[PDB]
Image (cartoon, coloured by chain):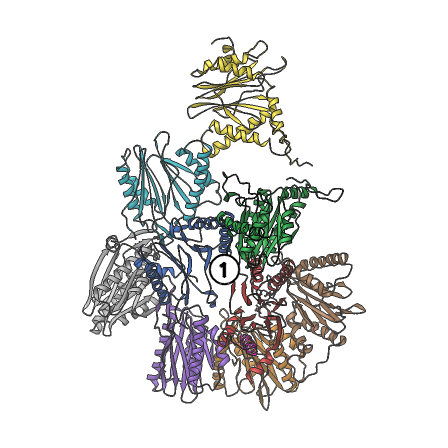
Chain colours: A blue, B purple, D red, E brown, F green, G cyan, H orange, I yellow
Amino acid sequence: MEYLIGIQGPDYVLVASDRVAASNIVQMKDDHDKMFKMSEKILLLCVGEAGDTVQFAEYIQKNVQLYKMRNGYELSPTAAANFTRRNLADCLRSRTPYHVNLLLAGYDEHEGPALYYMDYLAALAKAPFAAHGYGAFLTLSILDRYYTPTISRERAVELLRKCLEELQKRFILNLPTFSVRIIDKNGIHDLDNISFPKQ
Amino acid sequence: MEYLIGIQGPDYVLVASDRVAASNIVQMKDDHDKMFKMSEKILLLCVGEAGDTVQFAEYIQKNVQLYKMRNGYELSPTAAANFTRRNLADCLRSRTPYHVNLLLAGYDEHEGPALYYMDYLAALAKAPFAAHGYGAFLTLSILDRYYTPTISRERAVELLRKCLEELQKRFILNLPTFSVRIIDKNGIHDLDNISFPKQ
Amino acid sequence: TTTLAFKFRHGVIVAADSRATAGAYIASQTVKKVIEINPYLLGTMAGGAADCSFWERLLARQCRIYELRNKERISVAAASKLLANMVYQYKGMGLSMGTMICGWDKRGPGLYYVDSEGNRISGATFSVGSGSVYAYGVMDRGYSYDLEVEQAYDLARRAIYQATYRDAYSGGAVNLYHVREDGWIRVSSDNVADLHEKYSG
Amino acid sequence: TTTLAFKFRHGVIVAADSRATAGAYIASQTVKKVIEINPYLLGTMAGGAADCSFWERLLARQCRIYELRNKERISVAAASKLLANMVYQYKGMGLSMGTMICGWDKRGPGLYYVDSEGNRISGATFSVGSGSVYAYGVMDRGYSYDLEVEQAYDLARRAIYQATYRDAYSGGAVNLYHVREDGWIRVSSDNVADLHEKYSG
Amino acid sequence: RFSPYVFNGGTILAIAGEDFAIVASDTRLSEGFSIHTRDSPKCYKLTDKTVIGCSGFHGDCLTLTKIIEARLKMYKHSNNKAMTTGAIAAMLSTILYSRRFFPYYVYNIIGGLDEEGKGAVYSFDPVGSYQRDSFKAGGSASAMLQPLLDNQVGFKNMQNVEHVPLSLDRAMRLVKDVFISAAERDVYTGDALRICIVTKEGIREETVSLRKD
Amino acid sequence: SYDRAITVFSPDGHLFQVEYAQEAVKKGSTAVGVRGRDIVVLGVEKKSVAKLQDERTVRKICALDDNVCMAFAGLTADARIVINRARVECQSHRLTVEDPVTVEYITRYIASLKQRYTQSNGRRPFGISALIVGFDFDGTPRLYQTDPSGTYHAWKANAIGRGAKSVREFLEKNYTDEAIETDDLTIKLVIKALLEVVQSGGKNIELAVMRRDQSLKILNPEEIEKYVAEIEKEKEENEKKKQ
Amino acid sequence: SIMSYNGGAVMAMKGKNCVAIAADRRFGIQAQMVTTDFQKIFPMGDRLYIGLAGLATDVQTVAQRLKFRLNLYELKEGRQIKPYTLMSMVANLLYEKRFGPYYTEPVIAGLDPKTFKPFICSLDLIGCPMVTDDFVVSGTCAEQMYGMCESLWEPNMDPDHLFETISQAMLNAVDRDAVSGMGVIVHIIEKDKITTRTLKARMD
Amino acid sequence: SIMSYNGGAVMAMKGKNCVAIAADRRFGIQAQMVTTDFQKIFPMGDRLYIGLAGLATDVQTVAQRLKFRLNLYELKEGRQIKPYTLMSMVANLLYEKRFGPYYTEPVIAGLDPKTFKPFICSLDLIGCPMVTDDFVVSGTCAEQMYGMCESLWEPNMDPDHLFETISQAMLNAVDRDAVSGMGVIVHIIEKDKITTRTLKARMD
Amino acid sequence: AERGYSFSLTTFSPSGKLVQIEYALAAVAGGAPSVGIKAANGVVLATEKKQKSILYDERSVHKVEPITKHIGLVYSGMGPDYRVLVHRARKLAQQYYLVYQEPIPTAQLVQRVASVMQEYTQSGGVRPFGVSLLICGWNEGRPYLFQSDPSGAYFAWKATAMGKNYVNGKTFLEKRYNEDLELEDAIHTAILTLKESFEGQMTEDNIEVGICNEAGFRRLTPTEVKDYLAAIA
Ligand SMILES: *[C@](O)([C@H](C)CO)[C@H](CC(C)C)NC(=O)[C@H](Cc1ccccc1)NC(=O)[C@H](CC(C)C)NC(=O)[C@H](CCc1ccccc1)NC(=O)CN1CCOCC1
Ligand SMILES: CC(C)C[C@H](NC(=O)[C@H](CCc1ccccc1)NC(=O)CN1CCOCC1)C(=O)N[C@@H](Cc1ccccc1)C(=O)N[C@@H](CC(C)C)[C@@H](O)[C@H](C)CO
């Protein structure tokens, strides 16, 4: 079962996800990526049902890119978030609802760093930090304990490490490696994968 | 979810189990022991339902010890196995059935090394090697591929390592460490715990 | 609920909230979830209120009778095993109950987790209840066997606090007990509203 | 069913059994579970027989029309995405189907897993079917990207064999294909009864 | 509520020879514990080269039969040629899968001659999954018929035996034998056995008798 | 709905509506494009400089995707329609197929759309022609041209709209391997070809370039004035010292 | 219950020539809190607020579609909207989904833009209006809020007594509910000004 | 089905003055094989064998309790047991659990210890006896076994033809069943000797 | 069997004129004259209800129609078209009321009806309405008078006239009338401006008057008209 995490700093957004694609009792992929580039400064972390995730996420993505092509400028992280929330909410009472939980990370030239949280019921909420999946139940409290609004990206990465290590300690699911990226004024930056040399 | 494994050699029996006691989504114990000393040369690896495991296992254990005290000699691994199988089968259609899967390792002064496999339905079957739990589905084939009736205990330990490593690779459950013991003419010997330096 | 207990060098720390709900309705915020079995034996309490109270009280009775009969104090392992055996006979009948038996034994500091499901495991740290995960987070991120006393107090109190922050069914007041060799001592009983002011600013 | 595919230096190895059951009854042991989509595209087949056959055949049709229209060969990613999109529109309706799309692409050796559930993931090795776990065991214990051709053949064949040994719903004959840059080649088709004699003695 | 299905029994068999193809079936139509009729063969002549056997739910059998007829005619009008056997097999596959979510409760075995004159069987499942075989059984007594043919025609589990190709005569007696044996154990199989032989000459129809209990 | 045949055959076998649409294209501002080694350049003429109009909001060069750009000639509104539908298609292709889009593909889509509008009831042919330009994977630079009829072809260099035959002839007589051997030289070729028909300026010319794996880059009037200065200098250093 | 999935509480009170509207700030999923600053009260114009309790998604969605129709209304007609009019609008919007209703129970509080006459109403999930002269409540802790309001509310309250009343009601009702709380926000609106305060509350 | 949980197959055939009994060797749980040497045929004395197919536990248990009662019988009475007697014994033992039956269908094959007259019978899970002169089958692949036996069995077979017949029947029936197989064992018993062979079979 | 013409019957002439609308106006400026006067405390609508025979029953069909309890209608042009527009207007009003539970503002009803009239100048297979409408109303304290012509355009009037001699009537109202008038005075100058064209003995059955104050809209009884048509009262 999948795990997402977002931590917003004063001028950046740090995001991380697990790299496991599993079915039944086996891991079928150890390098799965749960993140979707939608703008040069917007990442969409989607998680949940089998096909619903990729389908919905790619739909939103291509629509954002379509906006960019049609208008010459990209959607703001907020406009993006409300766009996805609108789409997800519209399909909620339809024949084809998408069972997806998501995070949206972004940087605006005006509003700065932003992190958004979305229920599968399409309830959108902005937060300094958030997490999805069972792992969240073990990590959120930690984030409560150590997070400060002025936290530096180094300290943020260290905090993320505390969380992931906690997952290694208490969580019954495997989850050996993690995709980690950051977003600022210079767009999306891939960081070294937090991994634990199990076997 | 729990994992048991047994590999019988020409003059020894190698047994191993996971060290995880888990409830819900958290590991509650990282040094749980699934083995029960019943004779000086008999080990009982029990796994399954919450209280059923410990209750049944301890019942059998104390009854074997009672046999030893009453008669001055210990039950053979076979007699033990059929004793436990009788008890488990008797409670099967009763008000209080024990949902337990088990392995029985032993060494007889006459018959040598012996490994036994038991369904929760109390179906007893002798085998050169066996395994319990979901992990078995990933390890048994490996045991088919590399096991030989004349395998040395060093080679047996190495094979066990192959199995556990495979668990680290494909299995979605954590299972970082493993209890490993061997049984021969000199009784039960505790070996170094096979562990994988995750975190 | 949100009880937790961990053993270190200087004994066994035990902590809990005090909220009691009947659905979404908060029925009480003044519940003593740490039952004083013996002056050396404590029992945390989570799940069905009546179940926990009744069974741990009965456990206390049994331990007292043991003390009178054997002219010695019952061990932690024996108490936990007693409770586990009593509870197991009712397995499947719907008793909701998850408790921790803590104390000081002839084997030193002792801590056991006992389920209504049938579990009974010794361990270093434990957290039981609806907010157990949240407590587990901070507790694990701050635990050490070489923790000084006041540090252990801070760790436990804070863990229960954060738990009450995230868990909707946990709140009221953080209660804290310390189990030492000469018996246990009632450390603190700080309301969450005050701990908020203390921890935030 | 029990199919497996893995990509190494010298292309993409594909292997499968041939058993087809209708309950406990073995309806066939002569089923070609590796569909030849294009001379460069193969599709394994596990789950509902009619479902897999129909949908992969339709996939082949679509790929052919693509080849005619765009005057070029379809990519592995595009074929897998095509099948995934076709199948997704029937999600929840009860199609049982788990397939692997293998081939050689402009990006070199390509291997995708596509579900009736909605999955679609690229990867190095894959095993699909009732005996997939057993195959995963030996395949993982013997895999390397630097495997020589005959070694890869041995690994695949053996993995499917052991799978047929443990899985009651897998048997018949191990079929083996090799996907190279100039297309795929039908490597072997050894019956399990013979492979038993070969592997045991 | 209401069930749109009822099992009407019937067993079905096809064997492919070098220059022939046999399609046989019992003639018993039953429902529940009762006999509807003893004169109901499950064999249907499609073309001079192709015969189809359909067992299971009689409604879907009749319907599917008439559909196949109509579409044979359509193909004939469209391409000025008759449908080859394998083509009929593929078409049948699509037709069966067209009801993937409301299947014809029908077990189908097609027997005939290919374009090289050789014999061919095609076995189907109710939703279109088919394959080419030398010999196959279907219907109620299928599990009783199959193992013997695996032994006698496939020469399976037999050490140092010769692989002599099946002649029309031996195949015929084999069919009669497996049906006679099936009539002993299967309660849905009995009354009469109709056999359809397909060669370059055309289609012969023979009728052996089975017990009436 | 409006079920009326608009585009029909004439007794001489002509589709008058389509021809009329082509005449509407003929009235459009000139739009030329050339294909080079590592660059591709599109430039549009008479931008109707009113100097009170925002230049950005009237550009005749539009990007369809990160891979493909496009210029047009004819009715601007129709062109907006076609361009947007093309962009939507470019995204849909990514949705149904993991791979992006080839220039030939989107060109074929646009062409098919136009033709569909030449043969449908109640509709009316798009009064535009398009110069589509891109660098599809494999590196091969490609330029295509479309027509209201639905016909489409590939070109090394071409021109449409106001005065298209003149620039076509010029490009025919000037397209060499020596010319367009360098990026700046190809751009200079485009600017020269445009100057051979435009009302002699530079503030009337909009030029844009696509290069390698980079994004589309529009040229500022300063850079255009620089290239035009170099062109006016090469026309006095190789055409003045010989005539 | 579907309503109890997110929890929450919304209340409105009447004053002399002023009006009040309050709501808790917790956004939670069943038993876990996700956010402590979740907006449940939205301005539908100057001196007219709406407060939605229930399923968070439908709160946001109803708010947004209502703002849609409202904007169109204040554009077509050259005026601000009357409280009664807004109420009927919400009623219509909710009843359009009679057989597939949004799971939210809106509470409208404002002053007549022409007059100043205070106004409070509440509605069903299917849009049945109910206007009162004292208070209206909606949420998972409606019984507690009723308990406080029935004992604290007085008729002609000044903008200071109204604040204290609605604040004590909200705080003490919410403190007996597990899924409502994590802070309380109060808007006290009068002809001249609007005063927005967040109360000191329990965070457990 | 409960019977299909472990799978398996048991068959018995009559001969001239000999008798035969065969069974597969697979011990599996649903779809996974655990053992390839599982005993399903037990000797209830010299020249008298029983073969139990069905739920493995009840196979072993019925075998054990039957051996219990048998031993007590051959002790109380100074003789070996007759085939008919053993059959009635099993019938009684099974019917004692009429409303909580063992899930196994026993098949008895032997020779009359006094005479030599061959004997084969089978029973319900509730112990209804059925004696035949040709063959008896019990297992998950009963229909296949019936198919083979109805076409291969001849009356007066010598100890060599009987072996070939029961072997081909078992092999070819079992090879069309997914949960039966992994080897076949055959006991051909006659007045002078007992011959036990394990056949070459598919292991998939 | 039938379907419909999907093409506009109203198109632009080379000069730029929507000819069918202008012809519709020609139909309008040809029907019985109608005057409307807004008067501070109310509104008055008046029209020539001159039949063509003593056989006609003037108490069966009316030219002054109510839309709701507060809005009224008169017209100039074709009867049937007017009738259609009246039904449609009433329906629109009821929709507004069902949605908002508040009587529809006069301006809003005017705009909506105007949209309806606009449709028939562009929609397929139809001609525009040969009708101009005078719409009176009482909303939010103030009185309202509106006019809507076949093009779908609408204007707010203090006072105006339509139909035959609408120019002479417009100048008449422009001179012999102004603001601050009471309802009575307005009715008086309305019957007076109607008299500037009514060729014949203007009885109480030759003209129809409706009033709309802040107490609602209603049609004046023939008796009240008789009292007013006594050149006094
Ligand atoms: C695979 O999974 C391995 C062998 C493990 O089973 C193979 C792979 C492929 C490509 C052959 N899959 C099967 O063997 C598959 C099992 C399965 C069945 C149904 C759903 C999911 C998996 N077997 C079939 O599909 C089978 C083909 C035979 C070779 C004839 N067909 C059936 O079992 C018929 C029903 C399929 C169906 C009907 C209605 C709706 C959807 C699908 N079976 C019967 O008609 C008879 N019978 C009735 C009662 O017992 C079970 C089936
Ligand atoms: C009245 C309050 C103070 C006590 C409360 N009791 C109750 O809720 C009793 C129990 C009745 C019962 C019948 C049959 C069998 C068992 C129990 N129920 C009722 O009083 C009436 N209700 C009817 C409809 O609403 C819900 C309950 C309770 O036990 N609450 C538990 C939760 C619970 C567990 C099992 C069943 C029902 C509820 C609790 O607070 N547990 C805490 C610890 C203990 C020691 C208080 C923790 O778990 C923390 C706070 C999270 O809830």
Residue G95 visible? The answer is: yes
Pinpoint residue E60: horizontal percent, then vertical percent. Answer: 67, 58
Q: Is residue B190 above or below residue A3?
A: below
Q: Is residue F112 visible?
A: no
Find the magenta span and give its range: D145-163
Question: Which quarter of the picture shows residue D77?
Answer: bottom right
Residue density around tag 1, few if under 14, some if 14–19, many if 20 or more, within 10 Å: many
Residue depicted at 50% across the width and 43% down the height: F55
Tell me residue F174's x, y (percent). Answer: 62, 53
* Residue E49 sits inside the magenta stretch: no
Mark 1, chain letter?
A
In the depicted view, which residue is nearer to us: H139 or H189?
A: H139
Q: Name, please, the residue furthest toward the right.
A: E201
Q: Residue at x 47, y 9 (%)?
A: I233
- The quadrant of the rendered image in which ligand 2 is seen is bottom left
* Percent position of residue E190, x then y: 70, 68
> Closer to the camera, F80 or H157?
F80
- Main SS, magenta region, reads helix
Question: Which residue in the structure is indicated by mark 1?
Answer: A50
Element class at badge 1: helix
Amino acid at dot 1: Ala
Q: Quadrant of residue D1?
A: bottom right
Q: Answer with left or right where residue F202 lies relative to residue G80.
A: right
Q: Is residue G200 above or below residue B94?
A: above
